[PDB]
Length: 419
Ligand code: NA
Image (cartoon, rainbow, N blue to C red; front, top):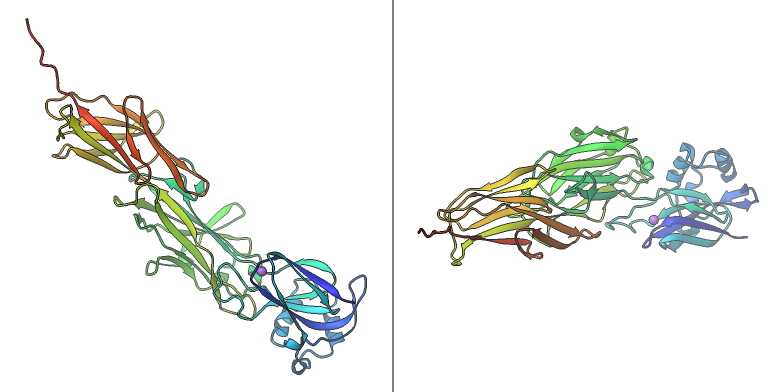
């Protein structure tokens, strides 16, 4: 008679090892009788545990995740033999091992099979009776998601647009693995590349989030800028209210430089978590999550001041307004100079009004131009389209470079005839 173990929640690219711990006879109620040591336990190390039947009897009835069982699992891990080993290549989702001799098996990932492999982790060492059932593998990784607050709402997303006058809030959400409780200690280091075209405001806070509440835990972390923006704690177990269901949230703000990337390329940052990847035998190996990217788009509104003779004209000055409600309020003001060109570097989608606050000598003051910018960002976070339209004016756009160009034509007054 042989048996089957099926592991759910498995990933591709693993080699699971089953070590035969106890032999015996399994009945219909999954009671194991006539127990001897399997070949999975090294003959030399069997004396340390004693008689097999009595050792089985000592554990009989104890809960699945009790302390006595997990202690035996760890002790066994140091007492294994290849003579009772079955190795199986993993599959994504479900991994099945059949043709097993009756009895008790220890399951683990193969030693060194996952070193420096991103987004993976060694399973907590399992003990299973082979009994034709499916069991969830006791293996899981933390996740990290980097997001930025939407320009036009409170919700956080992968990509948005912002202006030079805005504060740009970022949020990094970390989940912990379901088997966080099995670790004696847990290395936790978040690295963020930060954004090339932005200045970090240095207002970083860390939060323990669970049960609909947040507690600031910022002082427990080492926050450095020697190698990206790194938020680290040597051992997250030192924070005793952090558990498998806890979320760690990092929030900071930033502002665009006036050299920020314009258009479709955008201003991106990547972040990843470095985490303890093996809960067994107080291992201190680490692995990294895949990068999580956020992107911030911005544009450049250029005015070119000309007259009807198609000459460039100096001495104009423009005040840009943004509409918050019905209320228009000033965001930028370029005074009159010897320049005929005006760059509002760092503008986003929204409703604006443009006012010629200084008129050049010997020309009519233009009427105010109310206009609207739109950004089309697809669900991948990529900027697809941008527009700029007015009732009483026309713009030229280059969505790739992120240019919005307005030609303002100065008209001279009327030299009126007398009679
Ligand atoms: Na796995």
